[PDB]
Structure formats: structure tokens, C-alpha cells
Amino acid sequence: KETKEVYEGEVTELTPEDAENKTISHVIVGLKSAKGTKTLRLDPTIYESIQREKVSIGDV
Amino acid sequence: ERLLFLRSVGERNEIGFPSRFKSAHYKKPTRRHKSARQLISDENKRINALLTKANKLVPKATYFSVEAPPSIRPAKKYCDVTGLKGFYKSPTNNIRYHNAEIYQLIVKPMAPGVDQEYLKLRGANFVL
Amino acid sequence: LAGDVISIDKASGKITKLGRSFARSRFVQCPEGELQKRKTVVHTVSLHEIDVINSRTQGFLALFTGDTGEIRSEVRDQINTK
Amino acid sequence: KAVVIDDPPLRQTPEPFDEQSAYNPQSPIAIDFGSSKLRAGFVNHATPTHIFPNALTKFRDRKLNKNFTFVGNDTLLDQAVRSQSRSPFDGPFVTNWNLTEEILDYTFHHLGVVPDNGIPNPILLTERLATVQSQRTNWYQILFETYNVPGVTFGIDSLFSFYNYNPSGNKTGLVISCGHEDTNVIPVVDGAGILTDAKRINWGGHQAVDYLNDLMALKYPYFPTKMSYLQYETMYKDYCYVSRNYDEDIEKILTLENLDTNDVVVEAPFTYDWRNSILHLFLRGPRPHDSENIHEQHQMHLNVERIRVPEVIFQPTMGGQDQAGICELSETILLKKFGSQPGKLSQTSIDMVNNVLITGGNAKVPGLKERIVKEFTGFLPTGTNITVNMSSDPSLDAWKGMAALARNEEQYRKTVISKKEYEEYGPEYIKEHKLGNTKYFE
């Protein structure tokens, strides 16, 4: 038995916070669909996967 | 015979040259018939005069700071005659049209001097 | 260049040069009107091709090279259910 | 389906004049100097007594001194006197001063107010947002050294409507007004409009009728009869509504199954298949064209693009003005100002979202509130409660605004600009009360 949780929608804000200790601490991503918007904090691995997909501002 | 009805309803609201709603020292002036065009520009002249005499002062709420900024998202392009989606723009007269039939029946046989109104409705009337 | 009949797919960003038009100065006639048209494509894909595709260790080049190499049964069951 | 015809002329009022001689010499007078409708009345009455089209004429009559039927509803008796009846209001400002003196004299006659020096009553004016200083100095002149009014105050009519529907005077909200010649979005915090962050779109409802005139004249360059501008307002206020989603409607608005219920055909007064041809669907609707019929030459085939006219307050680039629509202005106000960021909302932004009021004479277009709340829940975070407030008639609720300010005594006396204060301070003076304009600087 497993859970499937999905965030779907258009990127409104993509702000990576660095907080060096070069290396990013996290990324704030704002998704938006027709029922409203939602903001997420993501680790740099998901930021690496996001920049793999050439994701910019305005992409579902 | 309806003219005397008009004088009958008009025979109730005469205001004399000494008006009864007067302050008894009222002196009507000969101020000019000022239009709505130059009032914005001589306000603008007053604001530049004030800021150049003050800076040698951020405005709070004027007629120009109240103005909405232009949009940051791209505007949707529409057909200039039918109002549907404008997929294509004609290279000659710069009219955005919908499909082939509108282009062949309206945009191609369009006379000179008719494109200016279509661009003026969109605010792109380049002829001054 | 000027004088080329081409085709553009907007979503995939693929431009195919169908050829030079009727300019005297290969040769293909100028296409009919109504640009940006919907085209219906009917694809017939054999079940072996989907078995090769769904097998993640097998690319579709094995559809041409022929080295599919004993596709597992569970991939075929997923393909049948799909 | 039998095709029907729609004659657009508007009837004539036979009873123009009604006034009462009995009046209170101490009760103030509330007048709303609207661009479209003049409103007038007393303080103790809840509804405005006099509704006028804010227009006057100078009728030239031989052998009776050439001065008759000057101001008001008296122009509505005949079409000939209503034809040249010049409303003196331009875009931002009224133009002629003797005309406005005649409006004020006529309406002061229509409350039955007797002379006592100039006027023995305080006045209650409505002033447009970010008013030109020359207008307010000449307004000070035409009250003080013309009518001797002891008490003047003025404010934004949208802020008046917000005070009417929120009589506490310290509420937080967002008012979106759409007047005759101007629309604006003003945020109110603690009852105080932050005009510093209010915005303005120069469309209103007059430019909507002008847009309909320009559209329907460019659609039919060979129309036989001249379509009157008053009839353009008449068929605008009857067949124009706002779509829920404009993008998916215009690709459906000219299909064959949609034309059966959407299309209404207007008729002007007097005395190669067509189904595949979408130009025939745009010009002549879902019926075949009979070019020999005298009705079809006069058939004013509207409603194919009845969605385009009210949509332009959301996309002003279709109207020619390079301004962001009220959706984007509301988005910037609720998501970028007052300490609010994209993603998390401040408490003032949440209270503003929870109290949204739309008003004005152009607000009675159907489908506005549903489009506003759907577009609001488009960009707002999920779970934020959105309440959009509406009136039964949102054109005259500003008059109820100055009536509610008149019932409150201590809120009246903060905003009163007297004759003595005007005399010591000159005509360049603004009471920075919360229900009105502010200073141009700090």
C-alpha cells in the first residue's frame, strides 16, 4: 500500500535560496492551477531535477 | 400645437439675471472654455515646476501616479475584424486576421485609408 | 532561404524543408491555404514494438538492429493490461 | 425558429417637474455630480429625491426671448430638444461653468430652498480621485463666492459606497468601481483608502458605448440609416454580458450550435455555402441572407461579438490603452503590497479579500461578479475565503454613502471645510480625512 501525492500546475515563482556554508540551500516554488496557488519548499535534488527539465517561470 | 406645451413647461423655471440663488456679491467671470486636454498638461507643468523648485520630494497621489502600469504578461492577440483569435497578421496593412476567408474577402480587398480605423480601435493608428 | 516550401511543427520545434518552390532563378508546388491546420495521423503500432519500448533495457533501435534479446514476460503482461 | 425584430428607440417622460416648497433650513443637501446621472436630495431621506441625466440645453425660440427648457428632465419631452442637449461633462472634468451654475440653480429650485444670503445649507459633494488642483480651486470659488455655502466636503464616490455598505468606518476592504467614464480599484485599510496604492483604468462605460459604435460601424460600412448614440446605449445595456472564461468562448462563439441561443438581431427603424462561410455567420448569423428584403438591409445584426464589449475592462489593450486590467491590479494589490508576498498573505490582505465591493453605473452588466470571483480564486491561495459584495442598483449607492456620512455627526465634523478655513488657508487646501482625497505630497 502506498500514497501518490502530485503537485500540478504553472510555476509562478522560482526562487532558490543559497545559504552557503555556490551550493543552494533550498528552492521556493509557487505552483498555480485554476483552483488557486500553492507554495512549496524543495531540496536541491528536486531543484537539480527541475533544472534538468529546463523549467522556467510560466511552465506547467 | 405641441410648441405651446413646450413654452408651458418652460414657463415655470425662468431664472432672472439677478438670480435668487445668489450671494448678493456674485460676479460671474469670463473664464475661457477650457477643454479636457490642456488641463492634464498644465497640471504636469505645475508638478515639474514644483519638483524642480523643491529638489534644488516624492509625490504621494497625483493624476499620474494613480495611472495603472502596463501589464507584464503578453497580451492576447485577436482578429481585427471578427474578434476571434488572430493567428496571422497581414504583412502589407498590418491587420491581424482569423483565417483564409476573412483574408481574401476583407483584408486583401481593403482600400487604403480603411486600415487606420481598424488599428485605431486597437490603439495602433500610426498615422498622426 | 526565400522560395522554400517548408513545414513547421510548433510544439516539437521540427522544421522540414519540403523543397524549393516554382522559382525559375527539388521543385515542389506551393501548398494550399489555411495555414496552421489540424492534421489527423493514424498510427498502427505492433504489440512487439510496444513490448520493446516498455522494456526499459531495450531501446527502439532493437526494432531495427534486432537485438531485443528475450523480452521478459511481465513487460508483456503490463502491455496487455495497458 | 421565427426571426424577431428589435426596435431600439427610447420613450419620452411626460412629467418632468416635481418639487416641494417645505424644507428644512438647517438640513444639508446631498448632491452627486455624476458624469452620467446627477443625483440630488436631502439628508433625512434614504433615497435620492431627484435623478437627472446631468445635461442641459439652450433652446432658441422666436418671439419669446430665445431662452426656454434649460436644465434637466425637460429635455426628455421632445426628441428635438434632446438631440442637441449638451451634457457639459468631458472625460475627466465638466467644461463650462455657467452651465454648471444653471444645473445647481435648477436643482436648488427643485428642493424648494428659499434664499438666505446665498444658500443656508451645507453641501455634500462627490469628487473624482486625484483631482486637478485647478478644479478644486474653481470648485471652492463656485461654492464659496457664488452660493455662500457654509459647509463643503467632498470625496471619492467609491469610498462613499464602501462607507455605505460598511457603516462602521474602520473596516478593511477593496472597492472596484466602474463609472461612466472611469474605472478604478482602491484598497481601504481601517476605513482609510490608501489612495497611494489605488489604480485607474480610463475606460468606464462611455468608452464601451463608443467601442460598440466603432465596432458596429466598422462591421457595416454601408448601413442605410444613422444609428443614434442613445440607441447605442440602449442596445448595449441589454445584450452585453461578461463571459466566465473569455479564451474558450471566442473559439465557440461562432459555431453553428451556439448561434441559436446567443444571437439576437436588432432592427433599425425606417419609414460557397453559407454554413461553411464563417463570414456569413459573423455578419448575418445563423439565418440565410435575403439581400432583397428591406428589413435585412436595416437588420442590425449584433450579438456575434456581444462578449467583446464588456471584456475590455479586463484586457484594456483591446481598447487601445496600454494598462493592466483590473484583474492584474487586484493581483498586485492583494499579493505585492501591504506586507504581502506571492505565496503568503498578510492579515490586511486576507481582510481585503474577505470584503470585496463592486459598484458604479457600469457594474450592472451581467456576469461581472462571477467572472471577478473566478479570476480572484485563480491567483489567490487555496482555502482563502472570497466574498464579493453587490448592490441591487450600484449606481446610486454613493448617494446613500453621503447620506450615511450625514447621519454620523462626529464623522461629519472631521471632514467639514468651512468658509473661514478656506479664507485663512486659501483655495489650495485638502482635509486629509480618510473618506476622500489626500495631499499630492507629504
Image (tube, coloured by chain):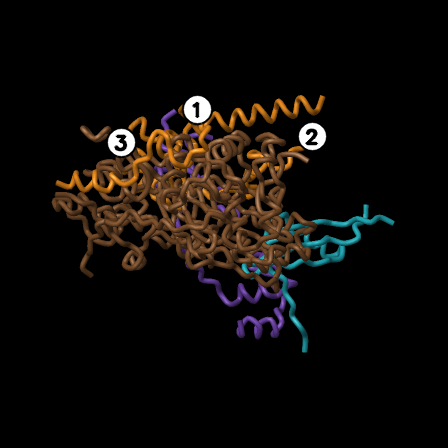
Q: In the image, residue A56 lies at what x, y percent?
A: 63, 47
Q: Which mark is residue D269?
A: none
**In whole angstroms, how far apart are the C-alphas of marks 3 and 1?**
21 Å
Amino acid type, callout 1: Pro
Label 1 residue SS: loop
Q: Does residue B86 appear to the left or right of D261 in the view shown?
A: right
The residue marked by circle 1 belongs to what chain?
A: B
* Residue occupying the point 42% across, 40% down: D115
Label 2 residue SS: loop
Is residue D74 among what the camera can see? yes
Chain ID for orange: B
Front residue of D7 and D425? D425
Q: Does residue D95 appear to the left or right of B47 in the view shown?
A: left
Front residue of B121 and C35? B121
**In whole angstroms, how far apart are the C-alphas of marks 3 and 2?**
52 Å
The residue marked by circle 2 belongs to what chain?
A: B
Question: In the rendering, what colour is chain A?
Answer: cyan
Query: How dense is the environment of label 3, judged by Cα within 10 Å: few (below 14), some, or many (20 and up)?
Result: some
Residue to which mark 2 is pinned: B57
Q: In the image, residue B78 lies at what x, y percent?
A: 41, 43
Chain ID for brown: D
Amino acid type, callout 2: Leu
Is residue B98 among what the camera can see? no
Front residue of B5 and D357? B5
Q: Which mark is residue B29?
A: 1
Query: How dense is the environment of label 1, judged by Cα within 10 Å: few (below 14), some, or many (20 and up)?
Result: few
Q: Quick check: D138 above or below C78? A: above
Question: In the rendering, what colour is chain C?
Answer: purple
Residue to which mark 3 is pinned: D67
Outermost residue on the bottom side: it is A1
Label 3 residue SS: loop
